[PDB]
Image (cartoon, rainbow, N blue to C red):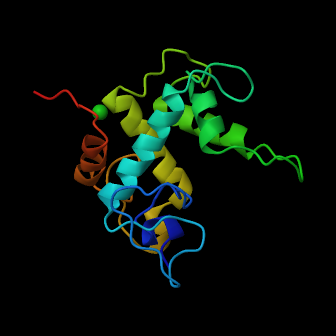
């Protein structure tokens, strides 16, 4: 059994809410909680756009700017309003900061930069879905491991991001 995000062409595990381009019609057989996309490029594109919507916000709930990996991941993976106190959001931010080789409170973060967005998207995909080797698949030689470099690039291109090339 593949992870839910990969089965759904929704490797970010985006919850139903916005009618992203490339969604399947929702039916009685649909995933009850998470978006299902017709192709991986559409799911990857939606993930890049969601992260851009957070980054483009001036201020977070806590009153602080949204201009750092910590503040972007706080929006992406928010804690619950009540129930058991748990620090999954802090661990998630630290893990993505390691993927970017940046400190979580570095305010030079630019998610309009192709390479920065690529590393954050790929980090989230690998975090949400685990190792392809755990599902008896060969990982691709990249951060995300589930999708080819070409599949990641097509998602990001569709989200408007420009990789400088020679
Ligand atoms: Cl790059």
Residue found at the very far bottom of the displayed protein: 28
Q: How many discs appear?
A: 0
Q: Residue at x 63, y 38 (%)?
A: 75
- Is residue 94 visible in the rendered image? The answer is yes
Q: Residue at x 53, y 59 (%)?
A: 13
Q: Residue at x 47, y 73 (%)?
A: 135
In depth, the one of 81 and 26 nearer the eye is 26
Q: Pick the quarter of the image with the C terminus.
A: top left
Location of residue 32 in the rendering, given as x and y in whole percent from the top left corner? 59, 74
Q: Is residue 153 above or below residue 60?
A: below
In depth, the one of 155 and 123 nearer the eye is 155
The quarter of the image that holds ligand 1 is: top left
Q: Is residue 7 above or below residue 97?
A: below
- Is residue 130 visible in the rendered image? The answer is no
Position of residue 7 in the picture relative to residue 103 (left or right): left
Location of residue 33 in the rendering, given as x and y in whole percent from the top left corner? 60, 68
Residue found at the very far top of the displayed protein: 108
In depth, the one of 32 and 9 nearer the eye is 32
Position of residue 156 in the picture relative to residue 5 (left or right): left
Q: Residue at x 49, y 54 (%)?
A: 18
Quadrant of residue 118 within the rendered picture: top left
In depth, the one of 24 and 8 nearer the eye is 24
């Amino acid at each position: 059994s593949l992870p839910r995000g990969i089965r759904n062409n929704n490797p970010g595990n985006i919850e139903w809410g916005s009618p992203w381009q490339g969604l399947q019609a929702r039916t009685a057989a649909s995933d009850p909680r998470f978006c299902q996309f017709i192709d991986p490029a559409s799911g990857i594109r939606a993930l890049a756009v969601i992260l851009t919507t957070y980054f483009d916000k001036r201020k977070a709930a806590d009153g602080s700017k949204i201009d750092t990996i910590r503040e972007v991941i706080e929006r992406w993976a928010p804690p619950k309003k009540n129930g058991v106190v748990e620090n999954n959001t802090t661990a998630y931010a630290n893990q993505i900061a390691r993927v970017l080789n940046m400190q979580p409170d570095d305010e030079t973060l630019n998610l309009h930069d192709y390479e920065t967005m690529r590393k954050m998207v790929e980090g989230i995909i690998r975090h949400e879905n685990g190792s392809p080797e755990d599902y008896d698949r060969a990982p691709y030689n990249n951060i995300n491991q589930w999708y080819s470099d070409e599949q990641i690039a097509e998602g990001l291109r569709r989200a408007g991001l420009v990789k400088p090339k020679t």
